[PDB]
Image (cartoon, grey):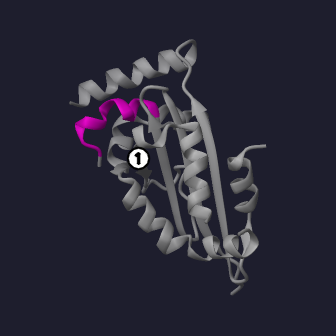
Amino acid sequence: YTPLDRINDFLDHLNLGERTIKGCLEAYSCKHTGTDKRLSISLEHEILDYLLLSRSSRKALIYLVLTLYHMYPDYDFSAVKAHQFFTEESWNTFKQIFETYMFEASKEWSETYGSLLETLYKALDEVVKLPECEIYSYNPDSDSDPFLEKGAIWSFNFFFYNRKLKRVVSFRFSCLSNLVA
């Protein structure tokens, strides 16, 4: 039972009255054998034919789409559409988002313990060496995409990728309205 398991339990259906906050960290090490390997190659080909993400992320992209497939393997992810829906970020741009939307969450957490953000950082750093990571948000517009939560007040899907380890932590967090009419 690690800090991620901690954060995750805390963020499992945090209920704050009218809106309910959900959050989820999942880590994935991309295998270099079997289906992961073949899939990776497929993606790498698709990307090259086609040659918003810049090209600096053409490799990162391969590994992000594997992590999608890992999370929802029955869904058709596509290298080109993801190229469209992934956006590169910085820790700082992530920090602002955490500050502005996960405010009630951080607050409840400090009331509970004696920062949620600091904890998160430490937890991520342990699993993917954070200062060496690349950061991405996934914002699909497609109706079907399973990273799209419909009727949500907001939703984010972040990804922390480590190139050396071929390792990705995905952080999803969203807000739901508990109202009735």
Decide: few, some or many residues near mark 1? Use Cα within 10 Å; few <14, some 14-19, many ≥20.
many
Give how far across and how far down residue 134 sits, in percent.
39, 42
Quadrant position of the C terminus in the picture: bottom right
Q: Extreme left residue here? A: 51
Q: Is residue 133 visible?
A: no
From the viewer's perspective, is 129 left or right of 84?
A: right
**What residue sits 49% from the left and 26% below the top?**
165
From the viewer's perspective, is 157 left or right of 20?
A: left
**What residue sits 54% from the left and 20% below the top?**
36
Residue 54 painted magenta: yes
Name the residue carrying label 1. Answer: 135
Q: Extreme front residue here? A: 114
Give how far across and how far down residue 172 sits, in percent.
57, 54
Q: Extreme right residue here? A: 1
Report the front residue among 73 and 109: 109
Residue 155 painted magenta: no
**What residue sits 35% from the left and 50% below the top?**
87
Q: Which residues are magenta?
A: 53-63
Quadrant position of the N terminus in the picture: top right
Q: What amino acid is labelled 1 in the image? A: Ile
Give how far across and how far down residue 149 sits, in percent.
57, 61
Q: In what element is the residue under mark 1? A: strand
**What residue sits 58% from the left and 70% below the top?**
151
Identify the image quadrant of residue 132. top left
From the viewer's perspective, is 58 left or right of 21?
A: left
Figure check: 157 above or below 107: above
Give how far across and how far down residue 21 sits, in percent.
65, 69
Q: Extreme top residue here? A: 33
